Amino acid sequence: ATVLDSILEGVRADVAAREASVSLSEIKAAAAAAPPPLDVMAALREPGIGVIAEVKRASPSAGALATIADPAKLAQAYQDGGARIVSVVTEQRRFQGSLDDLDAVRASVSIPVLRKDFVVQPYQIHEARAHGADMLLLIVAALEQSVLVSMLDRTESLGMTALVEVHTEQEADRALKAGAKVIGVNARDLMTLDVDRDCFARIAPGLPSSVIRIAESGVRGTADLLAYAGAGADAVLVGEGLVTSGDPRAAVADLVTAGTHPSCPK
């Protein structure tokens, strides 16, 4: 039926294959020995609309959307441009990412790193931590509530911050009830990658001031950033559709300039 169901089937298979090689006990030990997590909440508390910039496999080879293909070099461009956090897509089927891309990014940047994947079981949480993630995406649509709560608790126990992704007002209610500190709204369709313009603006007013509100989709430049800031975004996640013109550093620097301007809408 849904694209999400197919992604999650994929996750279960891909995780089972990794777990056959590196057991749950072994990945828990690897997480426990990893360099400590970086301070995501401090990054998010910095003044101005923060930019989370995303590394993913597919982009146009030329034109206004052209960017850097190599994950380490892209991530470095993002850090150089002033991104507060670098996101790296590790889901393997819809987005053709890999845990190797997380490793490459982690070695390349000294700012916090978000592992952007579809978490369904604790193995993935320890694995994220072992491979250096500081922030972890959790998706309400993927999880039954009690499991969401236990994944959120495990993420936090390991010293990471959860970015809890919601697609509807009811999912936002669930994220709040689960205890989320950071709630992202994703309005992108998994088939087309098009973004519903009304979703953030509808959901965000229901999110209390005590949560950090993230626009996970739809911000492609300063024009969008200003619109989302006015709608209540505290940070924006950019990547898909970003107008980079071959120069992602500059594109991120322009977003930072706009988001930290004293007169930026809010």
Image: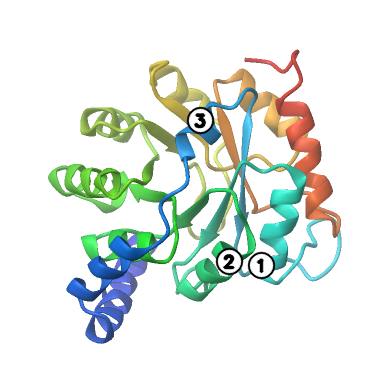
Of 10 and 199, nearer the camera is 10
Relative to 258, residue 236 above or below: below
Amino acid type, mark 1? Ala
- The kind of residue on which mark 2 rests is Ala
> Disc 3 designates what residue?
200
Give the side of residue 87 with respect to residue 221, left or right.
Answer: left
Mark 2 lies on residue: 107
Q: Are marks 2 and 1 in contact (CB under 8 Å)?
A: yes
Q: Report the side of 18 relative to 255 (left or right).
A: left
For label 1, count other residues whose C-alpha is less than 10 Å away and answer few (under 14), some (14-19) or many (20+).
many
Q: In which quarter of the image is residue 240?
A: bottom right
Q: Which of 184 and 167 is in front in this view?
A: 184
SS class, disc 1: helix
Q: Position of residue 22 (x, y in %)?
A: 27, 81
Q: Do the residues labelled 3 and 1 touch (CB within 8 Å)?
A: no
Q: Residues within 10 Å of mark 3 (few under 14, many from 20)?
A: many
Q: What element carries label 2?
A: helix
Q: Whole-Å distance between the Cαs marked 2 and 3?
A: 33 Å
Picture residue at 50% right of the left edge, 32% below the top: 42
Indicate the amino acid at tag 3: Phe
User: Crowdedness of circle 2 by 10 Å Cα count: few (<14), some, many (20+)?
Assistant: few
